[PDB]
Amino acid sequence: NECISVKGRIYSILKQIGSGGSSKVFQVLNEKKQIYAIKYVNLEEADNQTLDSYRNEIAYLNKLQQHSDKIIRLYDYEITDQYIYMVMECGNIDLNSWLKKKKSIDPWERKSYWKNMLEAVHTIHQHGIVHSDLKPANFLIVDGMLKLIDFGIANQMQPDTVGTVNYMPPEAIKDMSSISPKSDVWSLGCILYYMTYGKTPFQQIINQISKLHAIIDPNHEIEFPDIPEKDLQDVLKCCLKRDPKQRISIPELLAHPYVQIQTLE
Ligand SMILES: COc1cc(N2CCCC2=O)ccc1Nc1nc(NCC2CCCC2)c2c(C#N)c[nH]c2n1
């Protein structure tokens, strides 16, 4: 198969995991048979803005991983005026593909996944990033944890063999005319919801103007089927409050019993 050298090292291409824009992701193996992901970006045609988004991704990636191992790790990279090669921690699969296979989630793994997401999003917040477009696809499963991959600056990748609106916070939709960490809480809540109720809140409204409306509609109430874990019920409820000022914050979520008391009640 094709190969790829990166800063004086050779990797063999198992398969292509993903693509988007002028970039590809490959599952590869190194010299010693270990497994990695490599993102390749063809800069040939690339505006000075798109160019600076890739540059920004790499910098923040390099800074943020010092502060959390819930952020997908970047080990090495080559960047020229022609190309970018990023050698990264390779995920098993992304959370949106895993969810789409409809296998229901062990409650204790859902709770642990939730910790993972909070830790990751919390540390990007602590460096001034509000993702703004969080969705299942931003998380990869490795070492039995969820790890964040795309900080929503450089354009998001898609898996190889559309994209949705279901996680869009209300403030974002009301804002289109003529930015808060709370916005990520809403999207994180929609992911949790999905992990607990099998569906995102407005995943039934198949029509998208219809869907968009519900999200911003103070009198379209979101259902919250009662469940064994009541702390989980309460987390989803405060995460999906439409007034971002009443919505719960990450630092609050980190003090919340769902996360803090290990027996799920
Ligand atoms: C066998 O590895 C995988 C396989 C699958 N999928 C999808 C369905 C079938 C399958 O096997 C998904 C993910 C992985 N791992 C993986 N993916 C990556 N980018 C994939 C895109 C991220 C958004 C959706 C796709 C990166 C990555 C970057 N940038 C840095 N490490 C990475 N690790």
Image (cartoon, rainbow, N blue to C red):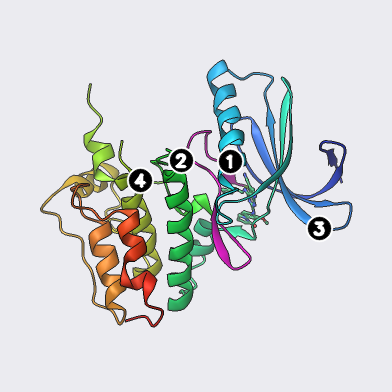
Task: Residue at 29% x, 74% y: name it.
Answer: 231
Task: Residue at 33% x, 52% y: name it.
Answer: 185
Q: Is residue 163 visible?
A: no
Q: Say whether residue 9 is left or right of residue 140.
A: right
Contact flag, marks 4 and 2 (Cβ < 8 Å): no
Can you identify the residue that label 1 sits on? 63
- Label 1 vs label 4: CA separation? 30 Å
Can you identify the residue that label 4 sits on? 165
10 Å crowding of disc 3: few (<14), some (14-19), many (20+): few
10 Å crowding of disc 4: few (<14), some (14-19), many (20+): some
Contact flag, marks 2 and 1 (Cβ < 8 Å): yes
Between disc 3 and disc 1, whose residue precedes? 3
Task: Residue at 58% x, 40% y: name it.
Answer: 63
Q: Quadrant of the C terminus?
A: bottom left
Can you give x and y, in whole percent of width and height, for residue 174 in the image?
21, 36
In what element is the residue under mark 3? loop
